[PDB]
Image: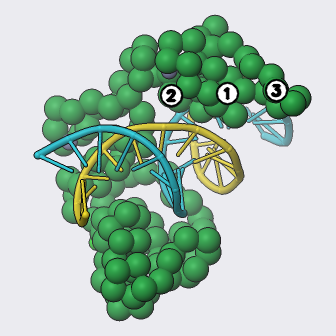
Chain colours: A green, B yellow, C cyan
Amino acid sequence: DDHYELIVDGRVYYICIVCKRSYVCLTSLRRHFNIHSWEKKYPCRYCEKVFPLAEYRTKHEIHHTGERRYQCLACGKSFINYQFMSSHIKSVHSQDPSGDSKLYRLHPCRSLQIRQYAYLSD
DNA sequence: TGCTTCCCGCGAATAACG
DNA sequence: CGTTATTCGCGGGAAGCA
Ligand SMILES: [Cl-]
Ligand SMILES: [Zn+2]
Ligand SMILES: [Zn+2]
Ligand SMILES: [Zn+2]
């Protein structure tokens, strides 16, 4: 295909034939390989930019709307992504949101049309 | 060296198939 | 049309960048 398989200790890795990156999941290799082949394009709906992964485009479009989905539950401040939220909580509140810490709320995305995870609304 | 974007295992949502 | 196949949102560490 666009990969070969490597097997060590009875565990299978899928290896990208172009850059030789390894993947535990074949769907991950397929997702990655678009970067090489560009057989699918994900163009921004607000500007001319085009991305090789759907999620890169989504994260990018959020910047166009200015929606702040990530909210610190200690002081209420909201942030556009996980990284700014995490940086805030570690720096201002001296706490780590990783694991399940319940230190932040991820609101559903309302400023554009993306797939909605049920767990975000209740 | 602090933003900024990328990366990939995981699995819920949904499209494609029957 | 219920069943499987596919897509891609999410965490949170890594890498890129000026
Ligand atoms: Cl908002
Ligand atoms: Zn590759
Ligand atoms: Zn854009
Ligand atoms: Zn806060």
Q: Chain of mark 1?
A: A
> Alpha-carbon distance for marks 2 and 1?
10 Å
Cβ at disc 2 under 8 Å from ligand 2: yes
Residue at the disc numbered 2: A32
Query: In this rendering, which labeled residue sits more in front, label 3 or label 1?
Result: 3
Mark 1 is on which residue type? Leu
Is residue A101 visible in the rendered image? The answer is yes
Is disc 2 placed on a helix, strand or loop? helix
Q: Are marks 2 and 1 in contact (CB under 8 Å)?
A: no
Write down the quadrant of residue A74 in the picture.
Answer: bottom left
Ligand 1, image quadrant it occupies: bottom left
Dividing the image into 4 quarters, which one contains the N terminus of chain A?
top right
Q: Position of residue A99 (x, y in %)?
A: 61, 71
Q: Chain of mark 3?
A: A
First in residue order: circle 3 vs circle 1: 3
Residue at x 69%, y 34% (from the top left corner): A24
Q: Position of residue B11 (x, y in %)?
A: 71, 53
Evaluate whether label 3 is on the same chain as label 1. Answer: yes
Q: How many marks?
A: 3
Mark 3 is on which residue type? Val
User: Considering depth in this image, is B5 or A122 the residue closer to the camera?
Assistant: B5
Residue at the disc numbered 1: A26
Evaluate whether label 2 is on the same chain as label 1. Answer: yes
- Asked if residue A55 lies left or right of residue A88, the reply is right
> Compared with residue C6, is residue A83 higher up or lower down, i.e. above or below?
below
User: Considering depth in this image, is B18 or A78 the residue closer to the camera?
Assistant: A78
Residue at the disc numbered 3: A8
Q: Chain of mark 2?
A: A
Query: In this rendering, which labeled residue sits more in front, label 3 or label 2?
Result: 3
